[PDB]
Amino acid sequence: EQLFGRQASLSNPRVSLVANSGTFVMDDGRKNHVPAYMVAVALGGLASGLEIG
Amino acid sequence: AVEPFPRRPITRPHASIEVDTSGIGGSAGSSEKVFCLIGQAEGGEPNTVYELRNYSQAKRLFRSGELLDAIELAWGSNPNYTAGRILAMRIEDAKPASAEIGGLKITSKIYGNVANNIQVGLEKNTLSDSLRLRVIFQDDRFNEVYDNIGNIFTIKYKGEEANATFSVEHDEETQKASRLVLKVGDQEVKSYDLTGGAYDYTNAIITDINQLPDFEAKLSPFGDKNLESSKLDKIENANIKDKAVYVKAVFGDLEKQTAYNGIVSFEQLNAETSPIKTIEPFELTKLKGGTNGEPPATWADKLDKFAHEGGYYIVPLSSKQSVHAEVASFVKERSDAGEPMRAIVGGGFNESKEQLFGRQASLSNPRVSLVANSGTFVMDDGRKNHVPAYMVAVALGGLASGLEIGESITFKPLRVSSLDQIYESIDLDELNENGIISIEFVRNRTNTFFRIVDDVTTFNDKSDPVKAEMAVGEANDFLVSELKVQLEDQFIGTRTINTSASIIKDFIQSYLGRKKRDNEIQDFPAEDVQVIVEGNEARISMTVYPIRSFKKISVSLVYKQQ
């Protein structure tokens, strides 16, 4: 519902809203539990690597 | 014709798999020609012709009936000679079912007695001052629900002034409500006529109201609501300073969403110049008045519907002699008009050969062939059905549709499980000599076949193959028709500045030579062509030898010593 609240406030094709939050295992073996905007980086880093098509 | 069903909109990318007793069934194969059928059939629009490419569409639209069984025979009779595309129209003049409750006239997209099993109802959503809808079609178990119906956006006035009022006016001449005015403290800021122009959409109104420093119009997230302004509802003096003032288009929201329902159409009840009966919640109630009607005494109007459709083969699923005459007259008309066709007919169970001769005596036409045998077929789901001849006629029609133009149905096998009567050699000869097409049984060491003995039309004379053998006549038919239409395009259709008789003669000879190079025709006389031109008209005459098939073999044996 809060996600829909953000959707209600914001509806723009130039932006996408990610909902899930999780944890990542990183260098040195440390695993960090992080908010969604860190997941957003993973989506952004992925999309950056993918080709245009 | 019309390919009725477009895509279903989808929501998510996924793969789903579900066990079932039955599959998707047959499929239309590549074909030069098209196959037309008429018969008893539940579902679909009466007096409308539908094109089918797959058995799934036939199930989805022609929900049940002997017609749907006929399609299965057409594509299931032989995988090698699978029948081509299909044109179908239901004989029964079914009716829709209707419900008129709660300010709404509700009618069924489905036509027939099934339509009365549709239930639709509205409910009041106390949580958001809105109406709610549910649609259930119990036979197909199709359940649909809509919520927050009618409410688009909310307005709040934020200033300290005593009173803010929201008003919408009504036009009685057309029953529309096309004004929306915001007033605060007996002073007006703006007024939006909802009759197009400046504020055609509610989107602009929301933008307009939001610009006002003392107001905010906020979009409801429950369902896309960008309706045109004219669809807003009658509203009279709503206090904008309060917690929430709703802007409502009850029918407009219903009109958009309900268009996507697969079962129902909605109309807004006019009272019985009468004002609008208010759309209000009501119990989920059955639709009523949907029936199958009765078939017409004459099928001529139905057959006239197929003119200019290109279906070479047409089969009526009936045994009535008068109906057969109607088709024969209709086919005769189309052939002269420039649309050649062939009709396949067969009536009743185990009908007497004398009665077959009675039909032959009444009817002798090269454009039609009469099938005598009746039998039973094993079909999908393991059910085996014992059926009249006109269902066998479909198998012949479906077979002939799959075969190439130059190849006859003669002697080809058939999958029919069994036949009512097993004609003897003499019995078969009498039928074939009298222009009756029949089925023959043979037995291998451990195999059994049902074969089509030969191609013969009701026309009896053996003198002219084109009259007798439909395969030969069909080859001539497609040859001429394909030639003329091409010729029309080059000279009549396309802008031609000049033309001579000899030029036409060369073009004709070029066309025929190409056919021989494709093996479509075996031989012909090159010098026999004639061309005459007379003002705006030209006469063309030519001859081509029909193909001859292999019929008789006689053998004798001699035993000897050593």
Image: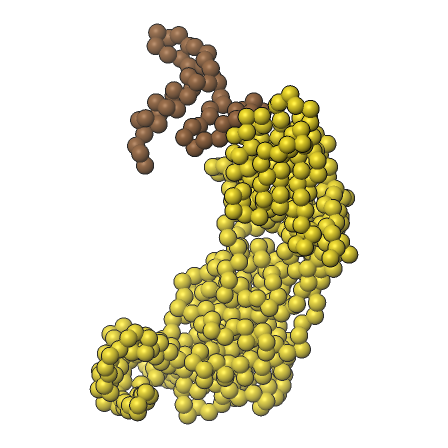
Chain colours: A brown, B yellow
- Residue at 74%, 52% (x, y): give it: B275
Q: Quadrant of residue B90?
A: bottom right
Q: Is residue B117 left or right of residue B37?
A: right
Between B518 and B302, the one lying in front of the other is B302
Image position, residue B481 (x, y; %)? 37, 78
Note whether B154 is above or below B543 in the view shown: above
Between B50 and B428, the one lying in front of the other is B50
Between A12 and B545, the one lying in front of the other is A12
Image position, residue B450 (x, y; %)? 50, 71
- Residue at 53%, 63% (x, y): give it: B50
Q: Is residue B472 left or right of residue B323?
A: left
Residue B246 at least partly seen: no
Image position, residue B558 (x, y; %)? 35, 84
Between B307 and B377, the one lying in front of the other is B307
What is the count of numbered marks? 0
Image position, residue B465 (x, y; %)? 40, 87
- Residue at 66%, 41% (x, y): give it: B168
- Residue at 64%, 78% (x, y): give it: B298
Residue B268 at least partly seen: yes
Q: Residue furthest front?
A: B187
